[PDB]
Length: 248
Ligand SMILES: Nc1ncnc2c1ncn2[C@@H]1O[C@H](COP(=O)(O)OP(=O)(O)OC[C@H]2O[C@H](O)[C@H](O)[C@@H]2O)[C@@H](O)[C@H]1OP(=O)(O)O
Image (cartoon, rainbow, N blue to C red; front, top):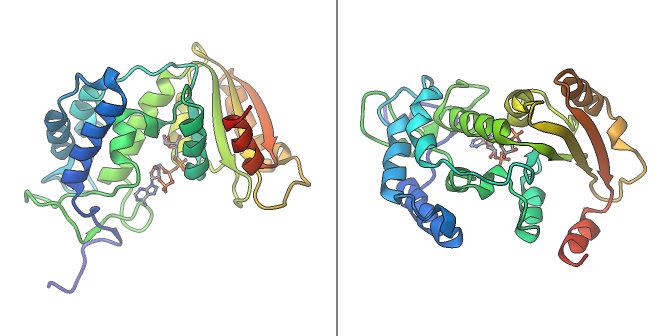
């Protein structure tokens, strides 16, 4: 009964509806070029993708109404992808305002850091628990959202695409991440000339060329097989890097 939670993962972020609406309004203020959006309609489409649906049965088609309302052209040559190093990627685009992560787009901004899910055959948002991607099920409202929007983002990228990776993780490139499983395989060689990785070093660990890490070799192989050039740089001093990006 009431002491048993449905799922293993965190539940919907508190005040999720109010937060998504408020973020939409704020985004349209910061980015007047997305001001045409009707934020109530955006919320209605977002809610519609998952309310009353079994949260292991969500599809990319469920999010298509939201994807349509959130259509946004960003400069295709100015895209920064990332994997497991969100804070530094966002700090970078806060300074370097001509480059964009997915979370700098309306749809990514709405969802960033939030969790949500519904309950099968009720109108209610589940604020207690939501599916864990590993322990429960992969086709859940959050995972499918990121898969859908990330595919579209990667498909739109062109020219030189950059990706920030965390050189302090055991898997610098992880093939089962959203970057590895969705984004890499949707970079189109007809549009994308080069994927350049920036491998961020942690602490005082600056003695190795992490572009030689086996997972980077793996990434390199995957990209080469898509007929896209691969480039890799070490960022040994991310503190100084960011300062230089601010004060070049
Ligand atoms: N369990 C979870 N519950 C809610 N959100 C989760 C989650 N696990 C991951 N996420 C988010 O889901 C999104 C995709 O992450 P994930 O599947 O772990 O793989 P990733 O390679 O690190 O994804 C980042 C890349 O995917 C997006 O397109 C980003 O723009 C970026 O290029 C991220 O916003 C995650 O935020 P996080 O870095 O964990 O703070």
